[PDB]
Every structure is written in structure tokens, then in C-alpha cells.
Length: 301
Length: 305
Ligand SMILES: *[C@H](O)[C@H](CC(C)C)NC(=O)[C@H](CC(C)C)NC(=O)[C@H](CC(C)C)NC(=O)OCc1ccccc1
Ligand SMILES: *[C@H](O)[C@H](CC(C)C)NC(=O)[C@H](CC(C)C)NC(=O)[C@H](CC(C)C)NC(=O)OCc1ccccc1
Ligand SMILES: [Cl-]
Ligand code: NA
Image (cartoon, rainbow over all chains, first blue to last red; front, side, top):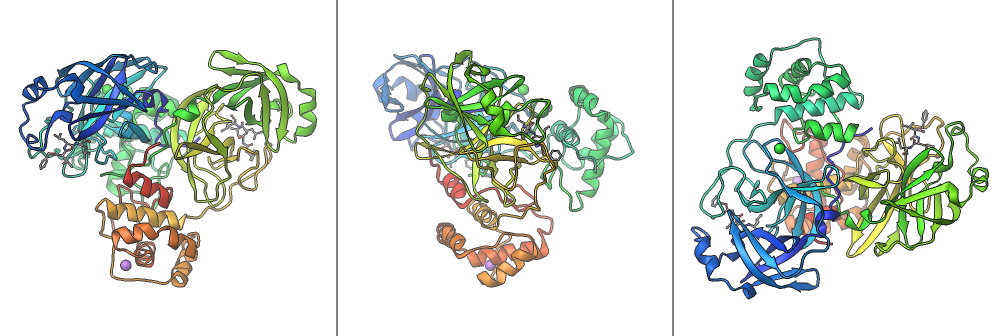
């Protein structure tokens, strides 16, 4: 029993983290096989942070301009290429610690673990979710760029996020490992702002099911709702629409608890209307939306 | 910016986890040098778990009764002994992945990372605190026994917890790596309960400092209090007493933010007596007490391991 925000063990990723320095900028890179992936803005200077021409900056670089350090070992760069907003540095040695891995681009509402790193060394590991507005709510300081997000279902590391930037509300933006930003952001210091964020409804429902699995029922009620009436109410609290895909996805947790999905929607409706009246659910006084249905099944079963 | 419940990187510990099987019970062990440590109740039967005489149950056991698997490799047990509630299985091979480590016993209010494991395979990592009632609010399923808690201090892993059991409220109990239970618990399936818990005051104060450092300031006020006055409020609201040593420990955060501890205590006093008036702090509608002062300084300064 118990329910915690649980990250994947980070050791398979720790063994991939390196430090990349170009000029006076240092950040982190991800060393897989004979390639180091990092944010391409490591090649910016303080003059071209607003409108960098990355193609023009990179053609001027020599391999020896990139200083890549893996623990105490300098790696030798022997070539390079840019893919969207990620730089791929070819090195003369393959990482002997390369795990089984893949690259996946995730959808809003998905969760992943972040291994926050500075100067190529790990600081800690935590769980995040891709918000509906394509930001994440991380914990990142100066130097954290190139830190990655990942899942490790089974024995394979799925890399889904590389950190690039912080926006004015203190939230974070980045790319997949093919260098495509999540959301409309660009790796330029021109004014940008995250959209109004919303709550990941399907994830809240999953967590309410987790609460029932863990022995709590105080928030249930005798009512039900149609899907459309649920979405008309949830709208008014800045909740994301619940789709029929989401209802299907909750089917297994529904079967395990005996609570029909639309009956759980009626419970959520009442919680939005009433609040918790001094009670908690799974140790929280707010409705939690950074556990997916898959996460709940992973941790409870 | 940002502030998250953050665990230590777990790689040094992942290389130490093994599977231990005795009879029909399988749980986890910790392989360090040429010893595997695991809960002694691995030796208990389905027919005999209510009032075990562990002394007597182990002499019947011999070495090849314990099946130890590191990944897909069997380790040969060559000796066995008991220390308090932990079994020590001597194996024929030293763990080549043994990190720099030590065994430590922590105090209530201290936090640590838990590497939850099943069948010798790490499955997840999360941050916990030793509650004042000596339980932890973990997440553990059948087969999780022998999962370990730890901190990292520079390059050294400090192991502080091994998981043994679940209490009726859904909270968890275990031992240090010398086999001493935390709390007034015993390793048998007799009636036991967690005591009434309290809130870890010095940790709440640390988390309020983290909030200020991240720009959440609405709860600050002009007032100050004294240690004596605040501790009466703390007692009243089932908060742990605040000692002068706690005040000194928070000193750094006090200097950095310009809010003296007794200044911040007057904020916490007001949040206890009046509540949050609908607002949140660092994304929480409750007062969070599982960040230590060290945890806050570490995360807010980017310390690495
Ligand atoms: C890499 O380690 C670092 C991580 C941050 C968490 C500090 N990223 C950057 O420095 C990044 C480089 C640019 C070229 C992508 N810049 C930012 O993240 C920057 C904030 C820094 C200076 C603290 N954000 C930014 O420029 O956002 C756009 C913007 C500009 C002006 C007004 C609003 C928004
Ligand atoms: C080890 O994998 C496992 C971890 C649990 C989280 C499943 N530990 C046990 O099975 C443990 C062994 C005993 C000898 C300490 N037993 C328990 O933890 C047990 C709950 C299990 C069956 C889920 N709880 C227990 O013994 O609590 C005391 C108790 C018993 C009966 C009535 C009141 C209190
Ligand atoms: Cl996805
Ligand atoms: Na004050």
C-alpha cells in the first residue's frame, strides 16, 4: 500500500551524462554509443542570443572547439551535425555504459523521470508531466540544460525530453531527442510565454482510482453523469476535455475497483464544486494530475 | 527555479540489489563486499509466522538453502549469521560494484531516498522522511522487503533503512542495516499499530524558506515570536518542539532571505492559527514537512554526486 510520486531508478541514465563546453558555455550532454546529444545553443555567444543563425555558427566550429568530458576523461570530437535544435557530436569512443534505449516523442499528460544534472554530474531525480501547454514544472538551475527526461518500462530507456530553457513563470521548455521543441517555443531569447495551463483530467481520475485502491472512498457519491455534461462542468474549472479515448483508457482501473468511469467523473464534479472540507486524498489537499493511468497500474499492481 | 520532491541518483545502490530466496519466500538483499544483507523473516514459513523463535529457526537452515541471484547469476552462499533482525549471508564473491558506503542510523525528521525493488530488480525511487512515530509513508507491494533507504554525502552512500513490514494504516516499518527496528515494532505478524504522528516543524520552516527563495512570499508578515511562545503553539497543533539547535541549523536560510527563524515562526504560527485562506505554497495546500534544511540548500544550490 501507499502512493508516492515515484521516479524510475536513474543509474542507466547516470552512466550516459557528460559535460559539453563550447566557448564559455557549459551544459550537459547525453552520450549514447559514439554520439553525444546536447542543446545546440551551447554554440551561442552572448551577442547572438536573440536571433542566432545556428547553421552559420556551427560551420565555423572546429571539432577541437567542443570540449566533452566524461567523468575524468576527455572525449575526442571527430564530427558533428545539427538535427533541429539538438547537436550531435560524434566522438571517437563508444560509451561502454550505453543501455538499451529508444527515443520517443510524448503527448501532453504523459509523465517521465528527470535526472537533473550540472557539469555532467547528477544532482537528483524527480517525476514530471508534459503539461497541456507543452511546458514542464521542473527544478532546474543555471547549467541544467541538456538534462534529460526518460521512462524505463521493462528494461529499455525511452528518452523523451531534453531541457533547453526556462520561461517567465518559472516553468520549463525543451525538445525531444530528435531536437523538436514541445510546444511553440524556439531556442532564442526573444519574448515567449506559456499558454494558460489546464489540469490533466484523465490523470486526476486515475489518481482518484488509486485512492480507492488504497482504501479511501469518502469522495464517492450516488450520482453519475454523461460525458458531455462532465466536460461542460470541467471546462469551467480549466480542466482539459475528457475524450472517449480517455474513458477507454480508464477501463481497467474501473474494472478493478467496480466504479464506472462516468461515476468517478461525478465524484470529481463534486470535488470541484465542494473542495475537500479539511480532508485529504492520498496525502494531498489538492487534486493531483501528474499520475497517468499507466503509472497507477504500475505502482498499485 | 522550481522546487520538487527530489531523490538522490540511485545508480550506486542499483548495483547492489540481489534476489534472495529461502523456501517459498523471495525478497531483496543488499550485496556489499562479500555479504548479502536481508530481512531475517525471509526464513519464516507460511505455517509459522506469528511467534517465531528466530534463534532456533536459523540453525536448521544451512547454506544452499539460501538462493541468491544477482541478475541472472547465482551467488554461492558460504556462511550465514543473524544480527538483530537482519540476516548476513556470506557469499564467495565480493560485489565488484560495491560503492564507498557506511551504515548509519537516522533520527526522526531526517529524509532519505528509497529504492523500491522486487525480485532483486529496482523498480522505482522516491524520497521519504522518518516520521516522529518512526514509520515511513512509503509505497511498497508484496515482495518489496529488503528494499533500502539511503543518502549520499559527497561520494559516500549512507545506508539507513531496510524495509520489513506494513502496518494497518498503510504506513511502513523497517530497520537500520544493523537490524535494529526504527520504532517500537517487532518482526512478526502480531497486533501492532503506528502511534499518533506529529508534524516535523524544522522541516516545515525549511520548506517555507524554499518557497521564499522561489518567490512565494504572501505568508510573510511583520511579526516575530520567541522559541518559548512558538513551542506552546507547536504543542497545541501536534507539531514537534523547535529546539535552539534547529534554529541554528536554519541559520543559513535565515541570512539568505532576511527572515529570521522566529520571524518565520510567526508566519508558521499564523498559518497554524488561521490557515492558508485559500492560497497555496510551492504548489501545495498543506504544510510540507518532508524537506530537511539540508535538502532545501542542496536542491536550491545544485549540489551533485
Ligand atoms: C541552459 O542550462 C539554460 C537553463 C535555464 C533553466 C537557466 N537555458 C538558457 O540559458 C536558455 C538559452 C536560450 C538560448 C534557449 N535561455 C533561457 O532559458 C532564458 C532564461 C535564462 C536567461 C534564465 N529564457 C528565455 O530567454 O525565454 C524567452 C523569453 C525572453 C524574454 C522574455 C520572456 C521570455
Ligand atoms: C516483505 O516483502 C513484506 C512487505 C509488505 C509491504 C508486503 N513484509 C511482510 O510480508 C511482513 C512479514 C512480517 C514477518 C514482518 N508482514 C507484514 O508486513 C504484514 C502485512 C502483509 C501480510 C501485507 N503486516 C504485519 O505483520 O503487521 C502487523 C499486524 C498484523 C496483524 C494484525 C495487526 C498488525
Ligand atoms: Cl505519450
Ligand atoms: Na514575521
